[PDB]
Image 1 (spheres, rainbow over the protein chains, first blue to last red):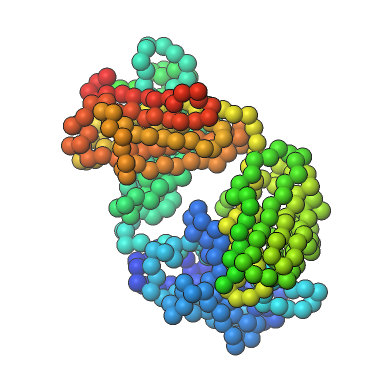
Image 2: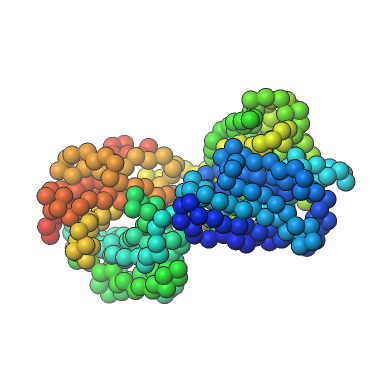
Length: 226
Length: 214
């Protein structure tokens, strides 16, 4: 009922601009102050900007002063965050948040009642690139055995994310798809692994399905022992 | 600028346990401290404001206390849906400030990792770069040390690590380590090894292959 809908995120090269939007519904919008909060991947929460209910007073973190501009539109019940001179340090998921009232009293400084779903901002000089997919072949140092491990190296793609399934979804037990790491080149790389019984090798085929929609890339890599 | 310091950074507990998280401020914030809950992929969720006032709908097992500089969040009996990250927030003054966060994890018995090493594929070798991957599978607790060695030479600055969350069925972790070399460097040496130090191991486990077909 009461919710904040966000939009405007995306991938942008360093030094460019972006404008975030937060549309409110279900509550009196222009009675509340409003805040923008961001959270870098793996990091914690950081407040970036706030504005009073009437738009007369605006507050900024030191990290964004002179660069970010907060504003609001009462007719549209919409909150804005104009972000200029973006740098990779600004890569995060951005939220709009509403300070909680205390028994009818609207205070801009309180715990944050309601949060938007978030919109992701990526600041990178990298260009869209499909992943290279390499097999992590299962091994042996005898002929028979117990449980074997095989996997899929999804390397050098941009931007996030890639989806990985095994045998078109028929293989889910023992699967670990690891979070991507950001390499020095600016491209991402992750690996998906699965543990199988050693009797399966040779009899059962293992196919790793990698989809990267930003580049319309779809790869089916069969992983067999060398 | 007021800075908040949460303690501890993480805690492992079982369902039914009593968990106590503290938040310390560099200045006095009277009673303008809020507590949040966050699960991966979702926005934060307010639990406490005014340092003791429960949000509407939040279970009564969540209690907040304290004033001035020292504060405390308490969960009187942990429930399965309470394993998440918890943040304190200061609302005494601008700028608004969050604590580093406290992650409450599922406690279980020690589990030693299964270690696997994977040589680079021949398809990648044609591109001019080689990636050796090492897998640590289903271990607990999370603390582990992976050291790469090539011809017994300890590597530095050419590897990256990635860890999953606790598995939904056995509460263990898994870890992937990727050593990245140039093909010329890779063909220049023979034995590639992955050394794993974990408290479930009496001695470090090393897995190794040697380049060729061995």
